[PDB]
Length: 235
Ligand SMILES: *[C@@H]1O[C@H](CO)[C@@H](O)[C@H](O)[C@H]1NC(C)=O
Ligand SMILES: [Cl-]
Ligand SMILES: [Cl-]
Ligand SMILES: [Cl-]
Ligand SMILES: [Cu+2]
Image (tube, rainbow, N blue to C red):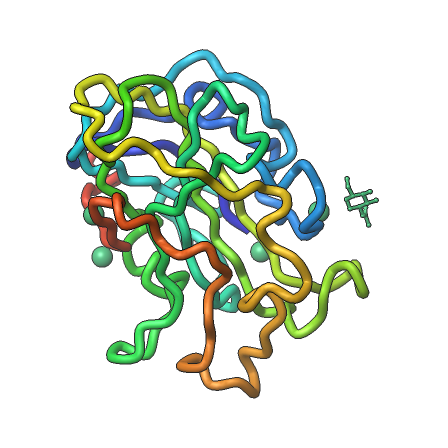
């Protein structure tokens, strides 16, 4: 159970974005229905009044929280992967539009899931803004908690993978458009009951065997990381 508070750009806090530049849902409940329109940008998908200005090559940091800013972030039970997608705003996230900029699942060296490292990062994970056409974009940050993912929601609605989905309105101003955005996948539509990484048993299956849901990360993606960029407690 987690939500996005706001974003940082190049290590500078853009301020509380809830219902302002984040299309915030009313609470931190997960989305579980893979076929639901709620998979696109969660349960209150509407245009919010601001869009955060960035340039290609900027570092865009999402900041998550549980109940209050810079708290326990997400229950340490909620092991799973993290991804970020982009689509043009014109789409409203409908159709084959979502392009993957970032994926982290299980790190063999540190023996840690993306979610474990997000807690250590005080809720902060980043992407580098790609060299796409200037204009208005949606960045969709997605955490998949796998603690009940031995079952499928479609078969047992009281279990299943849990999706914490947040859409940020981002305006890309300076970009030479040298890596124009390629075709995307649909949400809902990309994840189905047979997709690798949707049904998994984290209690019996080695985390080293976990494969995150496709699609693969776009070759045009400029970088990204789970790491604290800024100290919320200094405001
Ligand atoms: C899953 O979402 C689809 C599409 O909106 C809907 O028809 C179906 O009733 C949903 N399932 C549940 C259990 O609400
Ligand atoms: Cl749901
Ligand atoms: Cl960190
Ligand atoms: Cl980064
Ligand atoms: Cu939860």
